[PDB]
Amino acid sequence: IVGGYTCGANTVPYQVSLNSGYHFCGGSLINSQWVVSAAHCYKSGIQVRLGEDNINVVEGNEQFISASKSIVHPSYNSNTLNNDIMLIKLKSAASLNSRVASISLPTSCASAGTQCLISGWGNTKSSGTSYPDVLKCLKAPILSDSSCKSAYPGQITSNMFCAGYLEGGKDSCQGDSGGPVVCSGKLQGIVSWGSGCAQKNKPGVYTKVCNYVSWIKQTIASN
Ligand SMILES: [Ca+2]
């Protein structure tokens, strides 16, 4: 997260870190057994780390649970990032309390102008590289479809939305991938892609979670 703030430990209780020997992506806990992330975050041998603040220090609220299964969206295209969503099942159920909690799925899509909270452990610089140990946060609005398409001609599908600031300076970034965009207490987006980070006229692009609620529910019901 570039141009954000330190969230505070365990203030974003649905935020998870996906770990394969190291943090590589975010995700969102949606029930005791299941995490939503980006399909571009797929790999084998994932351990899901819940209750994290400093990802390099055991601070006392962590739950580390290996994944038993990953399900990439049936129509994910890695070239265009259309349908950039993946579900991960935990080998055991997480213990839920106020520091580790699920986030609700949307019942309606969000509108441009809605304010949201984007979070993660990704790069905090727009030029060059610095990875934080503690969770970073950014409040940002959803942008209009027209501004999003104008920013990224030929690239924005109906399964994507832009959020952030056209002026630059405030965005998600590498290492935030897969993590949440939460608006009014609902998971509306997944950190997906963008051109660089925090660049002028190049806002963040996010998977439009409201389009996938049916798929998520039916997949959980049968897996
Ligand atoms: Ca920790």
Image (cartoon, rainbow, N blue to C red):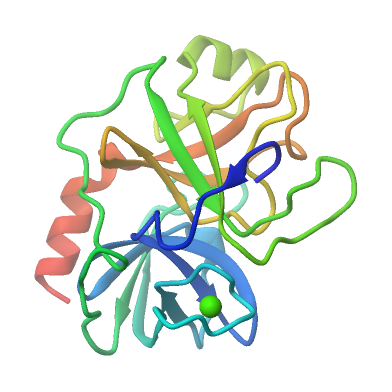
Q: Decide: is 189 above or below 175.
A: above
Is any part of residue 80 visible from this angle?
Answer: no
Residue 40 position, x and y percent, is: 55, 60
Residue 78 position, x and y percent, is: 58, 54
Residue 171, picture quadrant: top right
Is residue 60 left or right of 104 when viewed as pictured?
Answer: right
Q: For this rendering, which residue is in front, 131 or 5? A: 5
Is any part of residue 14 visible from this angle?
Answer: yes
Taking the spot 72% from the left edge, 18% from the top edge, the residue there is: 201
Q: For this rendering, which residue is in front, 187 or 72? A: 187
Is residue 25 left or right of 98 when viewed as pictured?
Answer: right
Q: For this rendering, which residue is in front, 135 or 158? A: 135
Quarter of the image with the C terminus is bottom left
Is residue 137 left or right of 209 when viewed as pictured?
Answer: right
Residue 35, picture quadrant: bottom left
Residue 191 position, x and y percent, is: 52, 47
Q: Decide: is 197 above or below 34.
A: above
Taking the spot 55% from the left edge, 46% from the top edge, the residue there is: 192
Residue 53 position, x and y percent, is: 52, 67
Q: Decide: is 89 above or below 197.
A: below
Is residue 111 left or right of 199 when viewed as pictured?
Answer: left
How many badges with numbers are in the image?
A: 0
Taking the spot 61% from the left edge, 43% from the top edge, the residue there is: 5
Taking the spot 45% from the left edge, 78% from the top edge, the residue there is: 49
Q: Residue furthest left?
A: 221
